[PDB]
Amino acid sequence: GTSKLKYVLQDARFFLIKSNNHENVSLAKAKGVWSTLPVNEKKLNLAFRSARSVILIFSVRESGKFQGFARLSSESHHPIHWVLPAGMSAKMLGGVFKIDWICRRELPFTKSAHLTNPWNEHKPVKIGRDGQEIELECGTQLCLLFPPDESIDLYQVIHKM
Ligand SMILES: CN(CC1=NC(=O)NC(=O)C1)Cc1ccco1
């Protein structure tokens, strides 16, 4: 069903999070961690303190899809063997966020064409810079479009709220 998912998403905040490659999403799915540049680290830390749930909705650049979504379980803290873009040192990253995956299934952008994000000029929700916040209603509807991930039990996530 969808009821525990809706409970986790109640009054949540949502952020569009890009990845440079599939490898880092794979690492994040296996290890329950994410790292960003300092600009988005600051935004996510502020949001983590502000809301019952902060949801990261992941999209590998140029893939045409979202690869799933996860809930922050921590603020950032300061080695994960990320596959970084050429010329980027691990020292340019902010800290590491712990995350609990809510859905590891993908959703193609074609399926979210009817959703617009008020915080990005009501452009289709797939459109946004890395770190773009997605307004509550749009973010909730987007998350509900993903195929159910029956491998995940949200019982333990609810207890972290
Ligand atoms: C794991 N992490 C991958 C990404 N995390 C993000 O938050 N945005 C991205 O584009 C890619 C490291 C990183 C931060 C910036 C570039 O590589």
Image: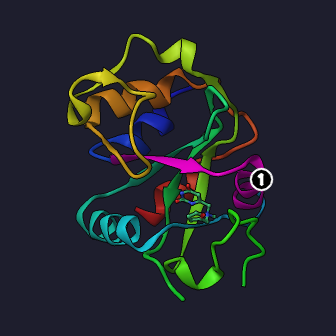
The verdict on label 1 being within 8 Å of ligand 1 is no
Name the residue at the front extreme.
Answer: 87
**For residue 33, what is the image quadrant?**
bottom right
Judging by the rendered image, the residue that carries numbered circle 1 is: 26
Q: What secondary structure is marked by label 1?
A: helix
Image x and y of residue 97, in percent: 53, 71
**For residue 151, what is the image quadrant?**
top right
Image x and y of residue 104, in percent: 69, 41
Please give the name of the residue rendered at 64% of the width and 79% of the height, measured from the top-left corner.
89
Image x and y of residue 79, in percent: 72, 85
Check the image and report above or below for 3 versus 35: above
Position of 50 with respect to 12 (left or right) is: left
The range drawn in magenta is 13-29
Q: What amino acid does circle 1 point to?
A: Ser
Position of 132 with respect to 154 (left or right) is: left
Please give the name of the residue rendered at 32% of the width and 47% of the height, measured from the top-left corner.
12
Instruction: Tell me the quadrant of ligand 1.
Output: bottom right
Tell whether position 111 is magenta.
no
Q: Residues within 10 Å of mark 1 (few under 14, many from 20)?
A: few
Please give the name of the residue rendered at 32% of the width and 41% of the height, measured from the top-left corner.
10
134, 63: nearer the viewer: 63
Please give the name of the residue rendered at 54% of the width and 76% of the height, measured from the top-left corner.
93
Image x and y of residue 133, in percent: 31, 46
